[PDB]
Amino acid sequence: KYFMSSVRRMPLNRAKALCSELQGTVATPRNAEENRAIQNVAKDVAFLGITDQRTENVFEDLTGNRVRYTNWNEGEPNNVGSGENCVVLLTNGKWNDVPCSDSFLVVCEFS
Amino acid sequence: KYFMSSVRRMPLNRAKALCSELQGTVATPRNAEENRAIQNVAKDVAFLGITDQRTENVFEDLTGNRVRYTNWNEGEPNNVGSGENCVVLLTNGKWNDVPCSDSFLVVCEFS
Ligand SMILES: CC(=O)N[C@@H]1[C@@H](O)[C@H](O)[C@@H](CO)O[C@H]1O
Ligand SMILES: CC(=O)N[C@@H]1[C@@H](O)[C@H](O)[C@@H](CO)O[C@H]1O
Ligand SMILES: [Ca+2]
Ligand SMILES: [Ca+2]
Ligand SMILES: [Ca+2]
Ligand SMILES: [Ca+2]
Image (cartoon, rainbow over all chains, first blue to last red; front, side, top):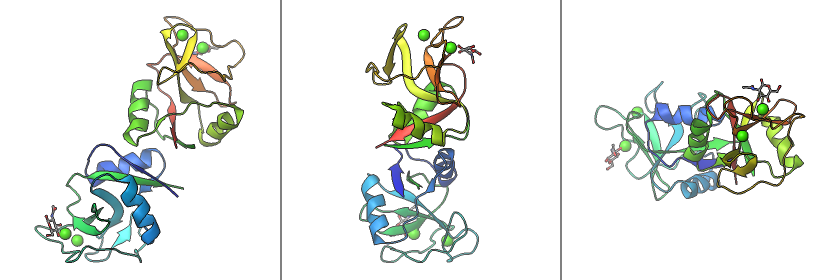
């Protein structure tokens, strides 16, 4: 598994399109080791390939597989405002759910 | 080095933008092993990061570094018509110079 980060920010739909263009997907850490590797390639807050768009509070990857390993920041996920169904990896390595329409860097994963 | 192929076709400038978006560059094979590795991922004719834009018949990689290894198809490079200053890897692994404005798949290189 190889991780590459974008230089520009974009919403999740554009992020998915970017990783998909090179036949990869938005990065989804499956353990602490991958979480750190992703954090390291990302120089700022970046999107992960995890959402609870299908079912609220049920987080799964972009292929529908419910995630097992999580690393939520204290107080997250909180689905605040009108809702937050996407996930970003903070600069300290913890996760926060955010609106999928907001823009962040993207880390793509390839195998 | 890791090589990934795009799914859509695009001109060289767009190909460069795609690869650089994930901090990589358009694939430039430095030997037959890498040439074969690029073949493995390119399901159809694809752009390589080489051009003779500066001086006709002097091929350099995208950073203006003159290349050493080449694998031209018989009869190539022929700079047909108004000129062909970009390079693509054919499905047999041999190269052909083509117009930089024409669209082809792109293979990106990372390391
Ligand atoms: C759009 C955005 O950044 N919203 C975040 C929210 O997701 C997070 O739960 C909260 C924690 O205090 O901080 C807000 O700023
Ligand atoms: C746009 C294009 O594909 N032009 C190619 C040209 O680059 C190549 O040298 C020649 C060899 O016969 O075949 C042409 O079709
Ligand atoms: Ca939610
Ligand atoms: Ca939140
Ligand atoms: Ca030429
Ligand atoms: Ca030619």
